[PDB]
Length: 253
Length: 253
Ligand SMILES: O=C(O)[C@@H](CO)O[C@H]1O[C@H](CO)[C@@H](O)[C@H](O)[C@@H]1O
Ligand SMILES: O=C(O)[C@@H](CO)O[C@H]1O[C@H](CO)[C@@H](O)[C@H](O)[C@@H]1O
Ligand SMILES: [Mg+2]
Ligand SMILES: [Mg+2]
Image (cartoon, rainbow over all chains, first blue to last red; front, side):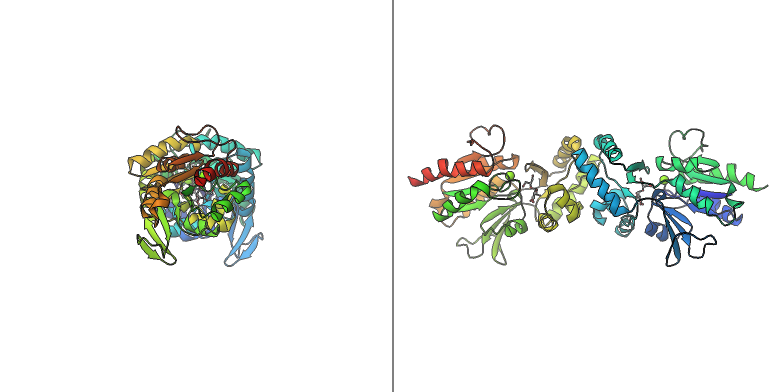
């Protein structure tokens, strides 16, 4: 079994804390179950949470592996080897400029905003916003509701793909949590361990995640995507419930 | 006679060129008629256009006078004396955070944007955008068309004022082109010369300018406000006609 999990609103709360999920995560580790973050966050953000590779960043845009991963792939970067799946940021920002001209109105993203503004909009510290701005593949957009559809089609018009991370729309191309997961499983050292995958998420950008796993669990608010398991409570309480009710009993085998 | 004039859309075309207004300006200067810019632009932008004081920046937020001005007012700053009429930008920005909390939606201004983003939205070069970002009083807002009214209501509810400069809304407190023109006329070294004021402009933020002068001329598009002259063509072509057909005859008598 491998557990692929979203971070904010799934494994972490609004404080960015594990809360009730901490005990659940410790139990999975005690049982030798790999837990792989699959997140909209940048590498810098993931590193700041103290998370170790392997992990998936920017909605599936990049797959980070330990420098010494048994199965060769990617490019050496310090204590990392990196695999790229989606288009590069500065190029995405280029299609956005094209979409802007098509839509006849500004389309703003994190790239257009100062760290101070990003911090204000997200409630992060300035340092944390600097990390959130350090994007390699995916752009986080700051759209107003009425233009949303207008902008989204304009995005779709110029061949960009969009998703929604729970609070913000994102623009990218080739960045897909399900695609990233599929690739990581294909690159797993122990094919037997990767044979059964679990996916936990809370937002639209986790739909691809759910479709790439064998047991999907939705811990978001409202109704879960079709066929996906739900939990009585959202977020970390959901994570904990999912581990206790759904995962632990299967591992007793 | 003092000629108070807006810059963009009045004296300058959409490319920032004088166009047909150049000979008109030269004629005024050759005849010793003071021409005083009264603009939404910052002091840095005005300087980059090669304009010497006196001039009025940021929608009336500040009056910049030659330091050797015979009527000592305001405070010395390098080669100028500055009369501050409006809240400082830092105070406006802080109050904008409150309007934003009230509105429940981001309210972005130039202060939130990179020079690169401001350049893109205005068609300015990056260097020009840096100058437009160097604001001392007034904030330029970048609002969703659909959110404008809610935002303007929020600004007012938290004690800020707003205007529109032709393309963008602005937020400030105490910046008014009319108040600024009145103050400058009151500070003029030669009261006789200040007794008759001409005002030329093209946008909402110029309506106070028209009220503060004795001969008002609108060179924007569509019909002029009540009590304000129109010209056959808008922009610098209107400035030229105004100088040739309205001002130079007044002067000759
Ligand atoms: O998509 C969103 O709604 C959130 C949650 O996934 O992610 C964005 O916003 C987060 C902060 O709220 C950042 O940490 C991420 O990098 C990203 O920019
Ligand atoms: O208000 C507007 O519609 C324009 C018209 O001059 O002024 C803003 O926009 C201009 C660029 O278009 C800047 O030069 C000014 O500083 C200001 O930010
Ligand atoms: Mg999430
Ligand atoms: Mg104008």
